[PDB]
Image (cartoon, grey):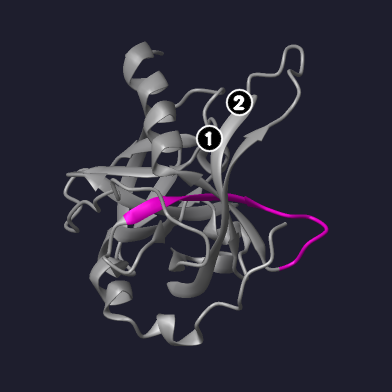
Amino acid sequence: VIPVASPDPALVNNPVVAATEPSVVKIRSLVLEGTGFVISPDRVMTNAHVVAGSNNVTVYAGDKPFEATVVSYDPSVDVAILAVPHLPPPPLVFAAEPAKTGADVVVLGYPGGGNFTATPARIREAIRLSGPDIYGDPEPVTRDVYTIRADVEQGDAGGPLIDLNGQVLGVVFGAAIDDAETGFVLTAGEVAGQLAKIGATQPVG
């Protein structure tokens, strides 16, 4: 882990939080709980492992429930798409330029499946996270990621990482086991590549 300065605690009150908050939603699937955000009208992107093979997925926009359906799931992909009809909040926009080391960012999500919380963060490093090719295992072998300094929790899974402009830099998908205050974020390029696999293979039963 590359060491960086502690995140600016003032980031919780930054207008960027209130601007993106309505579009960041809590997800409950049937016991399993996570975070998502609006990517396009009536469509929510979330963590695939949270909603994996679930027929009872609910989306909470502003403490109010909306029925969701997993319409895009691929076992080889970290992200999933939920279809959420009549969902008021507008889509969030992805940042077009990659984030740099030391930049102050914010993780938005629902840690422990509670209320919406903004977690102050700082970019450690942009890296290619490559593992071994596990035989018979579908999950990705390589990932474009940001390592971040942040007190991240499994409830933040599927939560967007947002810059000071209000744009999504990536999506929280993990943390370090031995290192506290260390989170792993899929880059906007990585999410695009993963959504591309789904866009290419659809429709699938």
**Which of these two is toward me, 128 or 26?**
128
Does the stretch in magenta take in 169? yes
| Residue 78 tag number | 1
Q: Is residue 15 left or right of residue 180?
A: left
Which marked residue is nearer to the observer: mark 2 or mark 1?
A: 2
Residue 15 to residue 181: above or below: below
**Residue visible at 27% across and 60% down?**
23
Image location (x, y in percent) of residue 141: 65, 24
Which region is colored magenta? 168-180
Task: Specify the quadrant that holds the N terminus.
Answer: bottom right
| Residue 175 tag number | none
| Residue 140 tag number | 2
Whether tag 2 and tag 1 are in contact, CB under 8 A, the answer is: yes
Task: Specify the quadrant that holds the C terminus.
Answer: top left
Which structural element holds mark 1? loop
Residue 50 in sight from this viewpoint: yes
**Residue visible at 63% across and 69% down?**
4
Q: Amino acid at mark 2?
A: Pro
Residue 72 in sight from this viewpoint: no
Residue 163 to residue 168: above or below: below
Q: Is residue 139 left or right of residue 108?
A: right
